[PDB]
Every structure is written in C-alpha cells, then in structure tokens.
Image (cartoon, coloured by chain):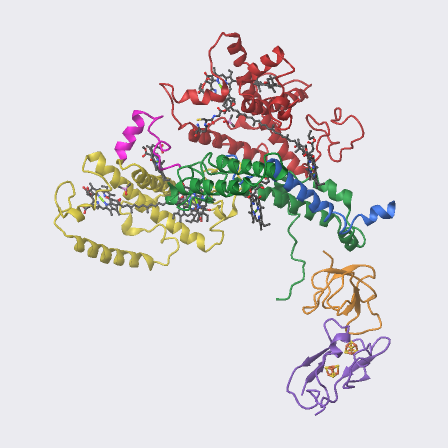
Amino acid sequence: MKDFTTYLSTAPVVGLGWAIFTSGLLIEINRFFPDPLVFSF
Amino acid sequence: QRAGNFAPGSEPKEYLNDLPGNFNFDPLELGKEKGTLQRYREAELIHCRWAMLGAAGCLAVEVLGLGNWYDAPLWAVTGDKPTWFGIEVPFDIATILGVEVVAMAVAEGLRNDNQDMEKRLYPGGAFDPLGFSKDPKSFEDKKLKELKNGRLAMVACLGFAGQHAATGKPILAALGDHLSSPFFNNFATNGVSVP
Amino acid sequence: EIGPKRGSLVKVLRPESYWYNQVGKVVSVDQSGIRYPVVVRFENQNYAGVSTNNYALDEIEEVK
Amino acid sequence: AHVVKIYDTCIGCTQCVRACPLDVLEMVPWDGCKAAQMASSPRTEDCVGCKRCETACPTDFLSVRVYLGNESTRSLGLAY
Amino acid sequence: DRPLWYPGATPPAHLDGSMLGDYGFDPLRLGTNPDRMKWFREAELTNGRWAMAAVVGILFTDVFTSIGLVGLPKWWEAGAQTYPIDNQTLRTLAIIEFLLFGWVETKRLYDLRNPGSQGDGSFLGITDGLKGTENGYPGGIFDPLGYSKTSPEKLDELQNGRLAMLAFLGFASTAAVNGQGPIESLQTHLADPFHVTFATNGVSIPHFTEF
Amino acid sequence: DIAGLTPCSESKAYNKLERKELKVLDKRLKQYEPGSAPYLALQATKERTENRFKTYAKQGLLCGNDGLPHLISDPGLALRFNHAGEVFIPTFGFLYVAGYIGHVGRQYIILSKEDAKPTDKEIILDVPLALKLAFQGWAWPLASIQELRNGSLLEKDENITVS
Ligand SMILES: CC(/C=C/C=C(C)/C=C/[C@@]12O[C@]1(C)C[C@@H](O)CC2(C)C)=C\C=C\C=C(C)\C=C\C=C(C)\C=C\[C@@]12O[C@]1(C)C[C@@H](O)CC2(C)C
Ligand SMILES: CC(/C=C/C=C(C)/C=C/[C@@]12O[C@]1(C)C[C@@H](O)CC2(C)C)=C\C=C\C=C(C)\C=C\C=C(C)\C=C\[C@@]12O[C@]1(C)C[C@@H](O)CC2(C)C
Ligand SMILES: CC1=C[C@H](O)CC(C)(C)[C@H]1/C=C/C(C)=C/C=C/C(C)=C/C=C/C=C(C)/C=C/C=C(C)/C=C/C1=C(C)C[C@H](O)CC1(C)C
Ligand SMILES: N[C@@H](CCC(=O)N[C@@H](CS)C(=O)NCC(=O)O)C(=O)O
Ligand code: SF4
Ligand code: SF4
Ligand SMILES: C[As](C)(=O)[O-]
Ligand SMILES: C[As](C)(=O)[O-]
Ligand SMILES: C[As](C)(=O)[O-]
C-alpha cells in the first residue's frame, strides 16, 4: 500500500490523472456547451 | 531658498538643494548628474522667457481686438500684407524668414559663446540697464518670480494650442464659453480630448 | 590553515568551468602545497558526469 | 599534424594514456599529491585525432585539447 | 485573537499578532510579508468604509420606496435617470470625480508611505490638523467619539464593513439574475420562501427539473 | 461597417452556406427510418447545427464577402462597438490560467530545492504538496506583483554564463 502510493507519483500518475482530468473537463464543456466561438459579450 | 514641495511629505531629492525655484519635483530622477542639470536650467530659463513673450502676445492680440494668434501668419496664404495694429507693415514672406534666420543666427551664436556658467543663465550689464539685479536680496526673489511666472506661461501656451486643436474657438472665446455654462462647456464634452 | 574551512561552501570563478558563480562545498583544501589546492565538490553533474574538481585559491570567493 | 597541448590543469590520473588507442602521450615527472604525474606529447607523427584522450580526461576544464591540423596517411587511418 | 473562522483544528501561521477583526482567516497566505499585510489592511479599510456608505443608499432609500412614501428609482437605473433630467450636470461627472479623488487619494497614499508626514507650511494653515494618529485612522476627521480608552470599537466598523461588502456583492448578483431590487427580492422571498431561491436562478443544473 | 465587413445576418453567402449544409445533411438523413438510432443522431446533429448558426448572430460578429465569421482582435475596434469577446477577454482568461499554472509550478519547484536529492521529487512528485499549491494559486496576480516589489524572484546574478 505504501510502496503503491509512492509508485503513484510518476508518469502513470498526474500526466495520466492530469490530462485525463483536463480532457474530460474540456470534452464535457464542449458537450453541454455545444459550439462556442465567442464570449457572451 | 526652497519654495515648497510638489507633494507634501515627498522624500527630498539631493540634486536640487541649492537651486532656485526648488520644489523637489524631478520624479523620474533626471538631471541627477551635475553636468546635465546646468543645461537643463538654461533650458528652463530660456523656454520660460520665450513662453512668457508668446503668451503675452497671444493674450494682447485678442484683448486689444486685432484677431487670433492662430490666424497670425495666415495672411501669407491669402496674400494680404501683414499688420501690426493695422499699420500694415509692407514686407513680403521671404524677407521676413531671411531676416529672422540671420538675426536669430547672430544672437544665438553670440549667446552660446559666453562660457560663464552663471551668466549663461542670468546675463548682466546691457540686458538689465535699470539695475534691478544690484540688490542681492531682491535679485533672488525676482529670480523665483520669473521662474514661477514663466512656468505658468509655459503651461498656458500649451493650453493655447491644446484648446485650439480640439475646439477651433479662440482663447477669450473659449474662456467666455466656459464661464457661461461651466458644467456643460468642458474638456470632456469636446468629444476629442477624452476618448 | 591555508584555504577556507573544510565543510564551508564556496563559489567558483574559473572562467572556463562548467560550475561558475554557483556554490559548492570544499572536500579538502590541499595543505601539502600545490597550485590547485581547493578541491570543491558539487552534487549536480556536468557534461562529463564528474562531481568534483580542484581549483586555485585566487579564484574561489566567499558565500552568497 | 595534430597540435596537442597539455595545460597545468592536471591531476595525473593516468587515464588519458590507458585510453589513447595510439600510445602517443607520455607521463614523466610532475610534483603532485598522491600520484604526481603530468601528461606530455613528445611525438605526433602517429596521432590520428580521434579525441579519445579528451573523453577520459576528468579535468575541468580539459587538460588536453587536440588542435585539428592537416591530414596524412597516419592521420587518415589508411591501410592503403 | 478573537474566535477562529474554522472552530476546530485550523492553525494560523502569521495571524497570531494583534490586529483589528482578526479571526485567523487567510487560506491563500496573501499577507505573509508584513509590509504587504500593512497595505492590505488599509485596502480593507477603504473598501469597507466605501461599501457601507453605498449599501445604505440602496437599503435605507428603498425601504421607503416599497412602503410607498417616496418614489425614488432603483439603483440599477438611478444612473440612467440622472442625465435625462432637465437640470443635468452631464458626464463631466466622471473626470471631475477623478480629479477631486486623485488630489486626496495621493495625500492618503503619501501618508501611508511616510506616516504622519505633512509639511509645516504646505497647506494653508491646516497642515496641523492633517496629521493622523495611525494609518487609516486620522485625527482631524472625527470630531467627537474618539477620545475613549475602549478604542477597540474598530471591531464594529470592520465587521459592518465586511457585512456591507457582502451586501453590495449580493445586490449586484441579485439585480443581475433576479431582475428586481433587493427589497423587492426580500419581500417576495418572505411571501414564498420555497420558490424564490438562488437554486431557481443562478445555477444551470436544476433547470432540468422535468419530474 | 468596420474593414468593409458587414454584420453576419445580412450576409447572403452565410445563409446560402447554412442552406447548403442543411441540404447536404438531409439528403443522407432521408436514408433511415424515424425510429432507428442513426436517424436520431442526424436529428441531434442538425439541431446543434441550426443552433450554431442562430446563436452566433447575437451582439454582432462581422462576416466578410465570404459569409464566414471574422474575429476582430484589436482593442479599440472591439471597443466603441460590441466585440470585446471576440478576442479581448479570452486573452485575459488565458493570461489568468497561464499565470496560475506558472505560479504553482514555480512555487513547487522552489519549495523542493531545500530537501535532499530534489531530483527525486521531479520524477516522484509530492502529490499532496502539488494539490495544496494547486488550490492556492487563484490569487496569483496579487502575489506576483507584491513578490516582485519584494525582490524574492530576481536572482542577484549568481548563475553560470560564458560570454
Ligand atoms: C510646457 C512645456 C513643456 C513641459 C515639460 C515639462 C513640464 C517636463 C517635466 C518633467 O521634466 C520634469 C521637470 C522632471 C521629469 O523627471 C519629469 C518630466 C514630466 C519629464 C513646453 C512649453 C514651451 C513653450 C514655448 C517654447 C513657447 C513659445 C511660444 C511661441 C514660440 C509662440 C509664437 C507665436 O505665438 C506668437 C508669440 C505670436 C503668434 O501670432 C505666432 C506664434 C508663432 C504662434
Ligand atoms: C466583495 C468584495 C471582495 C471579496 C473578497 C474576497 C471574497 C476575498 C476572500 C479571500 O481573500 C481572503 C479574504 C483571504 C484569502 O487568503 C482567500 C480569499 C478567498 C481570496 C468586494 C466588495 C467591494 C465593494 C465595493 C467597493 C462597493 C462599492 C459600490 C459602489 C461604488 C456602488 C455604487 C452604486 O451602487 C450605488 C451606490 C448606486 C447605484 O445606483 C449606482 C452604483 C454606481 C452602481
Ligand atoms: C467616522 C465618523 C466620525 C464623525 O465625527 C462621527 C460620524 C459622522 C458618526 C462618523 C461617520 C459615521 C458613518 C458615516 C457611519 C456609517 C456607517 C455605515 C454607512 C454603515 C453601513 C452598513 C451597511 C450594512 C452593514 C449593510 C448590510 C446589508 C446586508 C447584510 C444586506 C443583505 C441583503 C442582501 C445581501 C440582498 C437582499 O436582496 C437584501 C438583504 C437581505 C438586505
Ligand atoms: N441597451 C444596451 C444594449 C444591450 C441591451 O441591454 N439590450 C437589451 C434589449 S434592447 C437587453 O438585452 N435587456 C436584457 C434585460 O433587460 O434583462 C446598450 O446601450 O448598448
Ligand atoms: S586524439 Fe586519439 S590518437 Fe591523438 S593523442 Fe588523443 S587519444 Fe591518442
Ligand atoms: S587524462 Fe587529463 S587529467 Fe588525467 S593525467 Fe591525462 S591530462 Fe592529466
Ligand atoms: C481641427 As483643424 C481646422 O485644426 O485641422
Ligand atoms: C505598501 As507597497 C509594498 O504595496 O508600495
Ligand atoms: C446581463 As444584464 C441584467 O446586464 O442585461
């Protein structure tokens, strides 16, 4: 468990956890909010 | 000697201690070198004197009703001879410029060769034939007086050209406009001053 | 007795040295007498991968 | 040929000689700490300029630098 | 130090020192450097003091409007009613505002820089009264109500200023999505407290309450 | 009217392009029954395409002789008009996010220079420290300017140069 949590600080973590968070966030923003190309005002 | 601070409580600048008209101004910390400050004070005094003359003339033209300071040389394009109180001086366009160039050349060249660092600023002898500078205490006071009154004339003359550029009206006309309705006739209501 | 105290960190001023203006502890200032007495030790590698070097005493200077 | 130099920056590690493939440089008296040797280039007719002696020299900066010069049969490694 | 913002187990680092309205709230550690803390203190003071005199114009003036005594307009269009007025000092207002402020804001600026530093013959004969006891707490201004020993009433001022800054933020956030004024929103919310709520206006999710 | 461009509602080419797209969609939309999945997919696609074309034409965005939208990037032309969102506020939003990122990364890489073998921390990150700094950088403009006045970001010329 300890060595596993230590292993979870490398490429297989943020760099995966990161950029997975970001791809998901961007895809969800483009899905709920379909086609933005200019701000509200 | 020091006449005041531009901002009360501002930290003094050691460059300007023994200078006339000291207000602790220089904020960009120019003239810090001991050599440039002399030239810069020649600039002050000479610009102040030229300004004061120009402002006096611009005001006098309109006060006595002869016309506009902006329309002064403008006759050169129509061709009508120039006038000083309608005396109708007869000289042409090229003669004026030539005599100006030669006279300014002679006078400025004589002025430049003084090499008396204190007289390059405050000449003596023939330039004050009345002898107002003989009294040491009154001389400093009149120095401060001309410095202040020329610092006004320098700002006024820039206000002359700035006013005319946004609104073509003359000096006294714009002053009367403002004194008529102060809150309406302003520089933000020009439409050109502030975008 | 010649060079800086051992264990005291010092910087480098060898103009041609990978380690320049940055600090490094001294291994042992050579007391036997030689032109490059101060042996400084650095943790970060160089282009060659070496960690230590010996310098002259007219080149090293004080701490930051 | 290849002008080889050896500066005073040296510790006498005896490594740039057990690494040179052409046995070009020697190590004769130097007043050091533990080994007390300094490198020298007595002969250059056989030096090819491979810069293998500059890779093993741990001195910072390097103690030996090969000033590239003109080529010959030895300097071009030509068996023909 | 007065009670903490989190009641339990949240240690402050540099807020153990005495200061007005200190509840140990600084999660982002923006006031670690003492000089910047000394600046942000005056920042709070000028913001709070300004928002209180503003929310009163929105609160105490609209309470009479709802009751029907006065017919003043709401603040989200009180600015538009002015210049259409017959006697309207048109928008030479903003620039004269800036001039008249600047002249005083610079005095306060240089006083914070050199505390209590007002030349002797700098301002006509009133140089004397312009010296401030402390930063952001000048003397010559409050006529009465400062010569007590219990000077730590500044807690009331700071708490009311924070409450009024929240008040104006809520005013701007309401009059932007609720469409009505603060008093009107309050009265509709007392009328029916379950339907008029930020959940129905401001968040995008619950708008899909399709059974 | 700026740059000879016209608001994008009065563009005959823009409406012609919308009609072209809708015809191209419907020609292969008519291949499936109204109950199947592909039909619903094409229906939703047409929905958000019509939504594209409707929602753009609000607050004003100029389309040229080609009918396509053209972003105005000059501050001043986005002012005196209604174009401040074309690219003026997105600039500040990206600046905010990029600040945020650089601030957090710098404070991380600085706070790691003190412990033994910092290189390890660059291949085995301090996840809780990174999470803490990630939720503390959204005031970075305040911290940056005053950390600049502070001087804790200027290195006093103690780095490796060659000249
Ligand atoms: C005000 C001015 C310049 C102002 C500059 C200033 C204050 C600089 C200030 C600072 O440097 C300090 C001090 C310290 C630094 O750290 C900071 C800054 C801020 C940089 C110039 C005026 C300059 C004024 C001048 C030269 C006036 C001359 C008038 C002339 C020539 C008029 C001619 C005629 O009007 C007549 C007389 C008759 C008409 O009929 C015909 C014509 C020809 C139009
Ligand atoms: C809310 C606010 C600021 C909020 C600050 C927050 C949340 C900060 C919180 C934290 O930083 C701390 C503390 C500690 C950090 O470690 C963490 C965070 C979390 C970062 C400012 C209000 C600021 C409030 C101000 C300045 C109010 C001024 C209002 C004015 C001028 C209104 C004027 C008029 O409304 C009238 C009166 C009448 C109308 O008709 C016309 C107009 C013109 C609209
Ligand atoms: C200094 C001095 C000195 C001298 O000598 C004496 C004298 C004169 C006394 C002085 C002065 C004084 C003064 C001016 C005072 C004032 C204060 C204020 C204004 C406050 C307010 C203050 C204010 C405040 C708190 C406010 C608050 C508010 C709030 C919370 C609000 C809330 C709300 C909201 C959100 C929204 C909704 O829709 C509505 C409501 C529900 C309502
Ligand atoms: N009146 C604004 C134009 C933007 C605007 O506010 N339009 C009105 C409709 S003409 C609006 O959107 N009102 C929204 C609301 O009342 O909530 C301006 O001066 O440019
Ligand atoms: S360049 Fe090669 S051959 Fe020449 S001395 Fe160095 S190691 Fe020997
Ligand atoms: S390899 Fe370099 S340091 Fe080692 S003995 Fe040879 S010249 Fe000296
Ligand atoms: C405004 As104009 C007549 O000076 O070009
Ligand atoms: C008081 As300060 C460091 O913001 O000028
Ligand atoms: C978003 As609004 C109430 O200012 O039109």
The residue segment tinted magenta is: B171-195
> In front: B140, or E8?
E8
x and y percent of residue E91 in the render? 40, 27
Image quarter of residue E114: top right
- Spot the blue chain and give its letter: A
> Where, quadrant-wise, is the C terminus of chain E in this rendering?
top right
SS assignment for the magenta stretch, majority: loop
- Spot the yellow chain and give its letter: B
B61 left or right of F130?
Answer: left
x and y percent of residue E190 in the render? 62, 12
> In front: E141, or F28?
F28
Q: Is residue B180 magenta?
A: yes
Q: Is residue E73 magenta?
A: no
Chain C is shown in which shade?
orange
Chain E is shown in which shade?
red
Q: Is residue B21 at all visible to an observer of this figure?
A: no
F126 left or right of B78?
Answer: right
The tally of labels here is 0
- Spot the purple chain and give its letter: D
> Where, quadrant-wise, is the N terminus of chain E in this rendering?
top right
- Spot the green chain and give its letter: F
Residue positioned 76% across, 86% down in the render: D24
Residue positioned 66% across, 53% down in the render: F155
